[PDB]
Amino acid sequence: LGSILPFNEETADRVSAYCEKNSHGIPDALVEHWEWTRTRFPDADKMSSRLQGSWMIFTARDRKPKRILEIGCYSGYSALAWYEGTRDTKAEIVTLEYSPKMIAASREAFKKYGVGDRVKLIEGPAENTLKTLEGEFDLIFVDANKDGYAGYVKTILDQGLLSANGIILCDNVFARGLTIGPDCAPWLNDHVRPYWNGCGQALDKFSAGLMEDPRIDVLLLPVFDGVTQIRWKDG
Amino acid sequence: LGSILPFNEETADRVSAYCEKNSHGIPDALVEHWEWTRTRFPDADKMSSRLQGSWMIFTARDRKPKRILEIGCYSGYSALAWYEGTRDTKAEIVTLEYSPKMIAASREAFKKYGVGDRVKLIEGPAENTLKTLEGEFDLIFVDANKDGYAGYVKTILDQGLLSANGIILCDNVFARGLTIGPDCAPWLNDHVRPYWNGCGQALDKFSAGLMEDPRIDVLLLPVFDGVTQIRWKDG
């Protein structure tokens, strides 16, 4: 038997709002950023919910990571979540982004937000800029091109970019359900179905490959759009 | 739009099985106890998958708590998961139960598994026994009587049973969706619906009440049957 409650669209949305009502919210400045991102960007679908911002901030305050790595910055929403969750420690936040528009968008938001230089944006293809990083990170958040997740994790592990007691959090691993199977997101609009199906197929192979890597513990958590947790096996 | 993917019953079960297939499984000895629990208590109407077992183990290996408290032992499945995930740190596990058949099942299981060295089962009304505990716990798992959650958490916080860096995880907070409202679980078996509706009312009052406590950060995570994370507010 299963670990997922079945909801229709209306009710899933309603239960999300219930979680937000009954979870501490994100700071006002991050709400304003979120609303702005939604207003400014057509592809604003790539950005998390307010609840997910709460989850990122909770996670940071709980784990207290010393360095955070983020693969995929988009409009900086999640970077600013990590920044908020780490004010007491002034953790370093390294975030990688490929898209010139998102790069500009992010520096813009980061500028505006008043973040100090502990937030560092590195520009260029992540598969390459990842390889150049020094040291190790306590929390790594992966949410860039879905067809690149397998490569990213491989580089993280190979070069020891994940600290001993760190975790990798990979986002959107379900591809709305299409990671599991083509008939698993019947509600998707026709114009985005080819995209999610492509992602789903790549994330399926990604997920399978993780199970073949004897260095790590893997937990695919059925929350949000699917979150894979990865840690170094103790073992 | 929200943070929860909509799935019909069939598809939700398929996605659940996908998560199990693509997460490290629980040990053979724990699979055996899981089977035993489903047989001995076939009317349990209990959500406790292998995946949740994987989650509990991953969580303990990750967080490395020095001591674990759980309120609601049932058949000892979760206690044994905690045991597995804390093998190399020798963590103390204190579990509270009041049902005589559950106490019986758990003692038999704990003896068969050989986990008595560091699993301590405390018998009696958890309301009262919880208050007798001393020290602090790094991880607290609450899954007992749902009308009790508010009183358990208040005792935990008032007596400082939660360590500074610890977390409380409260399970089944959604009551199958009925916490959010009576129309939120149309798939549910009507023979258990009065029961879960009653739980849902209590858990709604519980969730609202958590938001009024200035001492804590709260996140209601839409995973499994609803998991509330609680920590001390910084700080």
Image (cartoon, coloured by chain):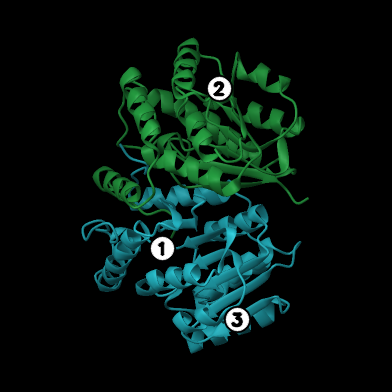
Chain colours: A cyan, B green
Q: SS for tag 3? A: strand
Q: Give me the chain letter of mark 3.
A: A
Q: Residues within 10 Å of mark 1 (few under 14, many from 20)?
A: many
> B65 or A190, which is in the foreground?
B65
**Residue position for label 1:** A172
Furthest residue in direction right, as rendered: B235
**Residue position for label 3:** A121
Pointer 3 and pointer 2 on the same chain: no
Furthest residue in direction left, as rendered: A183
Q: Quadrant of residue B32?
A: top left
Which label lies toward us, 1 or 2? 2
Q: Give me the chain letter of mark 1.
A: A
- The residue at 31%/26% (across/down) is B190
Q: Amino acid at mark 2?
A: Gly
* Residue A86 % position (x, y): 70, 63
* Residue A159 % position (x, y): 51, 72
Name above or below for residue B180 compared with residue B123: below
Q: Residues within 10 Å of mark 3 (few under 14, many from 20)?
A: many
Q: Give me the chain letter of mark 2.
A: B
Pointer 1 and pointer 2 on the same chain: no
- The residue at 75%/26% (across/down) is B134
Mark yes or no: residue B171 visible.
Answer: no
Name above or below for residue A71 compared with residue A52: below
> B52 or B121, which is in the foreground?
B121
Q: Residues within 10 Å of mark 2 (few under 14, many from 20)?
A: some
Q: SS for tag 1? A: loop
